[PDB]
Structures are given as structure tokens and as C-alpha cells.
Amino acid sequence: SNIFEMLRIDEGLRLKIYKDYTIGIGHLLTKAKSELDKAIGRNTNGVITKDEAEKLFNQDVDAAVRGILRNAKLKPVYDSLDAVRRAALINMVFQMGETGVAGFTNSLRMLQQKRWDEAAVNLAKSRWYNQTPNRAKRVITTFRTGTWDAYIYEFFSVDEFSASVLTGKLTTVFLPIVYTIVFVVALPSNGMALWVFLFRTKKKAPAVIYMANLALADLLSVIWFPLKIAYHIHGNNWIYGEALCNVLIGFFYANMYCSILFLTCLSVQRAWEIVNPMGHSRKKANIAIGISLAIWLLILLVTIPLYVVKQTIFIPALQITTCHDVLPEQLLVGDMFNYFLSLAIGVFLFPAFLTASAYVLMIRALADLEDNWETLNDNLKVIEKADNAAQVKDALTKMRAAALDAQKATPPKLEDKSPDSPEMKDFRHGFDILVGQIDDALKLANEGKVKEAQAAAEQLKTTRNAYIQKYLENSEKKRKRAIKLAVTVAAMYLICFTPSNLLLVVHYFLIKSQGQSHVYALYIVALCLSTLNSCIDPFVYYFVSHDFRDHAKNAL
Ligand SMILES: C[C@@H](C1CCCCC1)n1c(-c2cc3c(cc2Br)OCO3)nc2cc(C(=O)Nc3ccc(C#N)cc3)ccc21
Ligand code: NA
């Protein structure tokens, strides 16, 4: 009588009509007094006996089996199921009626094909699971395992490797310390950066706009850290509600992916202004705003399967309510794996490829412009110290080509200036005057007039400081900031993005493959070190924003 004993645990035993109107052991009356009097045979007046419950429950089971064999969609599955799983099917028919269970056409076909795991997942996403989760879990487990374990042992604790981490000092001492540091450092730093970009930056370039959302993504996550620190200090125990847990989870992964996308935009935008600069600083800004809105809305849509799933679970053995750290429904690991594998490819690797190659083109272009300005001054310094006509004509020729290449290059100042603008035409014209004078010294150098061409070098010095040096004065300083910028971003990927996304796939891959993951400790440290991006983000603003440097230095 295992089926009879199983149902008693699910339906309970009550001798009075109660709201789930039912009575006895899961005997449905109506959707109640009149339906009970003719079912028993007498006027029970709402209260039945302990003996009449058993007699009516034993008849409900015999009828639940007859309907199964009567049904053309329930009989073949029932004939394929082992006696343990047969009770689970009868448990559903006992609860949802013959017709209700017959609606699960796809899962019943899976159960017939002995695919217990696939059938379990299908049953986990239904109104049945939504209305009675604890009830459905026990029945679903009976299908998946084929044992009575779901009714013998109630949930008590997680795996040993997780239970030690959730009670160890790594989570209860190390994490809140690191999180506290980030809060003190990242909140006012990004707080001031957002202030500078909005109320102190009067350029409003596409770079400022991307950095403003970067600081905003930082702020919208760091503000919740006081609740995050308290969570860990008290032994990974959440007492603030399920909705507020899913908020922190949402804003955590949001800043995680906004940072990557806004890093790719900034890096590409700043690289694009050097290779092929344009001249619509007002339109390119509006575009950059729209791109930010598109990114902001795209992440709001992609973090939906994080807002809406149960992310809290009470662990009896630990007496704590964990947020995020433990997955309440171990049947969704298949969905979780694909989800974080999609993001790791399309929102991690793909933006990393565009981010890395952007600095490849950016640094090289800034390195070439540096070499031109250096070849110019060096060859101009040789002429004043060369005696033979060979070194004079040779230095003039190398200086000529150096100025012809710098003419095609974008000056550090005219970044948002289009190549057809007057500013660019005056820049190039400054070289046309210089190049012409080099030909006037080459005219003498090629006509054998050695010393007369050396005197022209002093004339070339005047043209350098007047028309050229003004634009290329601090081009080597701009290259150094770009290199440091490439280093800052590379470090942010090496510490905050790559360990998280890599382990996120590995973590859910092992729970899907073995039911436990030994990288659980690394998974937690990865997620912890991922929050450092908002502490490294101020270094990005320092190397990109010029107005932010002023407010950074003046403050300290
Ligand atoms: C557009 C922004 C705002 C920018 C203005 C300050 C409020 C945030 N935003 C972000 C966000 C926050 C971020 C971020 C990226 C995003 Br897309 O980076 C770090 O912080 N998450 C957001 C979430 C919501 C909502 O009601 N959801 C929601 C509610 C119920 C259910 C169910 N069932 C599912 C989802 C609304 C705006 C959100
Ligand atoms: Na960030």
C-alpha cells in the first residue's frame, strides 16, 4: 500500500470541510455540504469520522486507476511505467483528475520513452508547479528517480562543498571586507565622475556619454552593497524579501554586462575618431545617447530570466536563507547553462574581440603620428649639425616624407573635426607651407649649394613652431594615456570579466553534468572580484575624460 501512503502525505487527513472545499484525504466535493451528504450516505453536518475518511479515500484511489486505463492517452504511459512511477501518475490523476493529467501530452510521451530527466523539466514549467511547487517536486522526483525518496527525506541541506563555503569565513569575512572597500572607493569616485559628465563637462562628446552610463551602471549597483555586505556578515542569510533579492541580482549582472558593452562602445568610438574622424559632434552625441538607450533596454530584456525566477531558498541544516548563492530549483540547470553560455559568447567574447582590436588600431595610429613628429624634429636637428652635402639632402628627404604622412594624420586637437573642415584645411595648409620650404632647401641642396641649404633649416624652425608644433605639441602624451587605457581595460577583463563568465559556464555545467561543482568556491570569488570593475572604472575616466582629470586632481 505504497500509493495509499504516498497520497496521505500529499493530501493530509482532516475530518472537517476545509479550504485547500474538500474533506478527508484529498476528496474533492465541489468547485459542498450537499455533495458530502450523498457521498457518505448520511448527514455528516460538516464533520466526518476518522473511519469514514479511510473508506472514502480507498474508493477514490480505485476510481483514479479505472479512469487511467479507460483513457487512451493515459493507459499506454501507465503500462510503461514501473510501479513506483505508476503511483506518481496516479497521484497527479488524484489531484488534477483524469482529464487534467491527459493534457500533458508531451511529458507523457517522454515518460513512455523512459526519458525521466526531460519529462521532469517539462513538468516543472506548468501551472501545476506554479500553484503547488512543493507538491509537484515530490511527484516529479518520483518520476525522475523511480524511488520513494521524495516522501522519506525532506529537504535538509545542500552538497557538502557548498555547505562548507556558505558557512566558512571566505564568504562571511573575506567577501564583506572586499565589498566594503569597493563601496567606499567606487561610490564617491563614480559619484563625482557622473557629476562631472553631466554638470561640468560642456563638450558632450560621444566619449563622455558612454562614460556617463558606465558611472551610472556602477552607481546603480554599488548603492545596494550595504545590504550585500550585511548579508554575508550574518552568514549568507537574506531576510529582506524575495523581490529585493532579485533586485540585487538584477543590478549585479546588469552592471556586469553594461560595463562590457559600454567599454566596447567607448574604445571603438575613441578609436574611430582617429582612423576615420567625422564632424558632427552634436549629432554623434545624440546617436551615442540612442545607442546607450538601446544597450540599456537590451540588457533590461536579457536579465528577465533573473528577475522572475525564485532566487531564495531556506536551508534547514544551515538555518539561513541564501540569495543567489544556491539555486532553489535544481531542474533549471539545463536552462541556466545555455543562458550563461549565450551571454558568454555574444555579450562577452564578441564585445571583447571588438574591444581588443579597437586598441590595436588606436595605438598604432597614435604610434605612427608620434613617429612623424619625432622624425621631423630629429632630421631638422641633424641639418644644423651636418657639414657634407650628402647628409643635408638626405635629412631633407626624410623630413619631407615625415611631414607628408603627418599631413594625412588626424591632429590630437581636431578629434571631432571632420577632415573637410576649415580647421583641418588650415592644419594641412600648415604643412603645405613647410613642405614648399623643404623643396626650396632641396632646390639648393640639389643645386650643390650646401651651406645655403643649412641656413634654410632655421627658416624651417620658424614654420615648425608657428604652424605645426601647435597641433603636434602633446601627441606623445596622448599616446601614453591610450596605452595606459589599453592596460586598464585589459586588467578589468583579466580580473572582473573573464574569470566570471568562464566559471559561470563551468559552474552550471557541472551541476548539469554531476549535480555538484567543485569550482563553487572559485565561482564565488570570481563573482566577488567581478565587482572590482567599478573601482577600475574611475581609472578609465581619468585617461579618457579631460574634465574628469581636473576634478580628480583638485579633490586630492
Ligand atoms: C533602465 C534601468 C533604470 C535606469 C534608471 C534607474 C533605475 C534603473 N533599469 C535597470 C538597469 C539597472 C542597471 C544597469 C542596467 C539596467 Br537595464 O546597469 C547597472 O544598473 N534594470 C531595470 C529594471 C526595471 C524593472 O522594473 N524590471 C522588472 C520588473 C519586474 C519584473 C518581473 N516579473 C522583471 C523586471 C526597470 C528599469 C531598469
Ligand atoms: Na561598471
Image (cartoon, grey):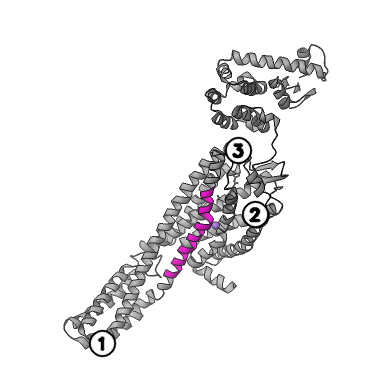
- Which percent across, then down, holds residue 367? 37, 68
In the image, what residue occupies the spot 76% across and 13% down? 39
Q: Which residue is mark 1?
A: 455
In the image, what residue occupies the spot 49% across and 48% down? 344
Marks 1/3: CA–CA distance: 84 Å
Q: Which residue is mark 2?
A: 170
Is residue 96 shown left or right of residue 466?
A: right
Indicate which disc, 1 or 3, sits on the residue closer to the N terminus: 3
User: In the rendered image, is residue 76 in sight?
Assistant: yes
User: In the rendered image, is residue 251 in sight?
Assistant: no
Is residue 424 shown left or right of residue 505?
A: left
Which residues fall within the magenta stretch?
A: 479-503
Kind of residue indicated by mark 2? Leu
Q: Is residue 235 above or below residue 453?
A: above
In the image, what residue occupies the spot 60% across and 22% down? 101
- Which percent across, then down, holds residue 114? 54, 25
Q: Which mark is residue 330?
A: 3
Indicate which disc, 2 or 3, sits on the residue closer to the N terminus: 2
